[PDB]
Image (cartoon, helix red, strand yellow):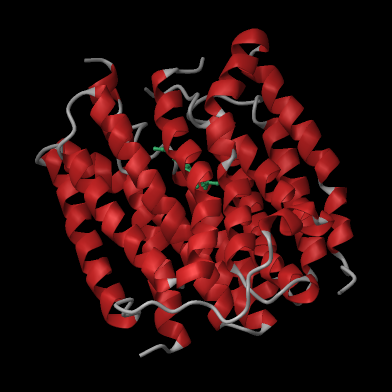
Length: 377
Ligand SMILES: COc1cc2c(cc1OC)[C@@H]1CC(=O)[C@@H](CC(C)C)CN1CC2
């Protein structure tokens, strides 16, 4: 009733449905907008990520205090509510409210799920493979969001995508209730490491910063696009590379040494974003997006297991707070990317900002090298 494969499949389907509900509202954004960079789409991107950043550490403490399954089930009882709220959203305020709920549900699911994955798969290699599979599920969600949403919303109606996603969610929630059975509390054995200590560390800082700055590029590029069939096939070149990269490096990273794969993933992000401006909409902006996605997938699949590795090598073997920190770093892009990046743009323009990002990415790339051999304690 607790085989590792089942929990891995849980986290897979969790991140898949979460990101599908995330990106399925894209064909529904203009239908609430019209009724450079955008401000309203910026707020739609912001609110959820900001609430996720607000709620990640508190979830990382809740899991250590009552267990993982109850957080995961709270996530899957929230997402089912946010989906219905979406399905019954007319104005802008209700849209933002539903997005923030969805954000709390996401934060919950992602943090507690990565924590359970690191807690079950105790060994390394297998944990690398497992994190790769989970991020591949996330990628599959990002891929299957836009086209599914577009086709349904354009075929039968605008409520149907949200309601079908609600049904899929409910099925996922039932599966999870069968596999995990959170009907009883279960606190972890050891007292978790104080978050202040985990944050004072250099190495977790370096890994989290690498994730954050490898995500910031594609986080600032998207909410400022020529859009808002160019809407459904908008985010295909990014996700079709994210998946192919993560579900290949998750299994072939430890053999090379993550430190090398992380450095290469940051370099590739940099060289892709730097070349973004040399493009047009249909012909140009595709291939650089593919490079960006492949590289950020490499970086994510290389840096997600390291977090648990660092904690096992230098702290008490608990996985909640550290993966909450990793998720905070990953999602900080979409909170300070649209608004602050939008202001930087409207001051200087996007053909300049992307270069700046590329510079900071190429500078932060060799800083991963200090993830070669962290001295234990
Ligand atoms: C509708 O809201 C949003 C829309 C989308 C996203 C973010 C938003 O909100 C958080 C994700 C975030 C990711 O994970 C990116 C993965 C890349 C690297 C392949 C891709 N974009 C796609 C669009």
